[PDB]
Length: 428
Length: 49
Ligand SMILES: Nc1nc2c(ncn2[C@@H]2O[C@H](COP(=O)(O)OP(=O)(O)OP(=O)(O)O)[C@@H](O)[C@H]2O)c(=O)[nH]1
Ligand SMILES: [Mg+2]
Image (tube, rainbow over all chains, first blue to last red; front, side, top):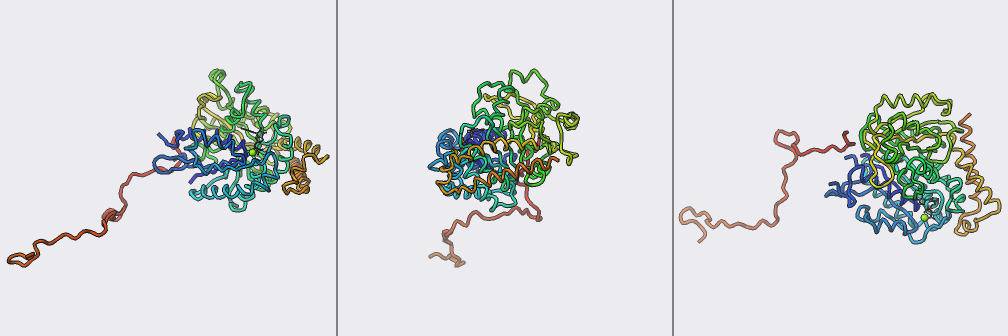
C-alpha cells in the first residue's frame, strides 16, 4: 500500500533523480548503502536485512549521465537494471527518440516498470520526470507515455516537465522538440507541471542569493517540490492530500491539466534567522508573481485553482487566516466558476534540512500547484519560434531522415493552437 | 540370541535411522482454545507524529 513509481527520462531526468531520490533517502533515514541504522513505502522497499531499494527507472539513450550514478556511491543503492541505458543518444531529435532508437530500449523500460508495479499493493501515481527540450526526453519519453496509457489505463500519470525557457535555450532545435511533444503531455498525461530553468535561476539569485548557480542547485528546489507533493502520502498531518485529490480539486475540464509550481520558504542561513518564516509570510511569498517556477506572470491570468501544501509546525487556524488575506487582494484574481479554490494540506513533518547544499533550517514550508489561464503564454512564446523556423523548413531534414513525415509538424502546431484556444475560452 | 532369557522380548530393539529428517514440523499460529498467538506486531502505515 501507498507506493509511487518515479520514471526519469532524458539527461535532466537522471540528474533530477539524483536529487529527488537523495531527499527521499534522508527523509526516511536510509544510509547511502540502502540500510536504515513504514513511511518509506512510497519510495523504497524492504529486501530482507534492512535493504531499501528505490522505486525508479533511470532511462537514457546516452550512457554517460547514467554511468556517473553507476560508478559513484549509489550503484549499491539502486538495483543495477533499474538504470536502463542505451548506445547512441537521440541527439536533440524528437524523431530519433520516438520512432527510431527509442523503440529498442522501450522494451526494457516497460518490463522493469511492470516488475516495479507487481510488488505494489495499491499504487497511487507515476511521477514521470523529463525535459522537453531535446532528444530522449522529448522522444522516448513521449513513447513511454503511449505505452503507459494503454497498459495502465486507470493509473494517474503525473509529469514534471522542464519546458523551454524564453531567452535561455542551450539548444537551437529546441522549439521543434517542444511543440512536437505536446500531445504526450496533453492527451496521455493527467497532471502537467510546467517548470523552466530561468525561474529557478531567479529564485536562486534573489532568495538563496547564490549569484552563480549550477544545474545541481536547480535540482535542489525541484526536489523540495516533490517532497511537499508526496508529504501526505508518507507522514501524518491535519489535512492529507493524495495524488487522486491533486487531480480532482485542482484540475478543471480534462484538457486543462497544466499546473505551475511555487515553493516559497526559499531562504538561506544569512537571512533565515532574522525573519519570522510563519504561515502568513511564507504564503505571501508563495503567491508573489515573481516566485513562480515558470517565468509566467500570473498577473495577466486567472487562478482557476490552487493547492497550498503547508509542511511543518503549521496550525490550521493560521492556514485559514492566510487564505483570507490572499483572497482580499485585487492583484490576485480568480475565474468566476470558482467560489472555493484552495485545497489546503498540512504535513506535520518539518522541512528536511540541507547540510552543505543551499537552503537553511526552516520550521515550516509551503508549495503551490496552481492551475491558471496565465499558462497560455508559455506556449505562445514557443509558437513564434516554431513558425519562424518552419517557415523556411529549417532543420526538418534531420527529422524526416529517420521516418518522421513532414505532416506531423503542422498538426503538432495545430494541436497547440487548439490548446491555446481552449485556454482563453475558459476565462470568459 | 537377541531375545530375553525368559520373556522372549527383543532386548537389542535397534534404532533404524530416520530416512528423512522429519523436521521443520508444525505448531501453527493457533494456540489451544482456537484464537491467535502473540507474535510481535507491526504498524504498516504513515509515520505517527
Ligand atoms: N533542471 C535541470 N535541467 C537540465 C539539467 N541538465 C540539462 N537540463 C536541461 O535540459 C534541456 C535539454 O535537454 P538535455 O539536457 O539535452 O537532455 P535530453 O532530454 O536527454 O536530450 P538529449 O541528451 O539530446 O537526448 C536544456 O535546456 C537544459 O536546460 C539538469 O541537471 N537539471
Ligand atoms: Mg539525452
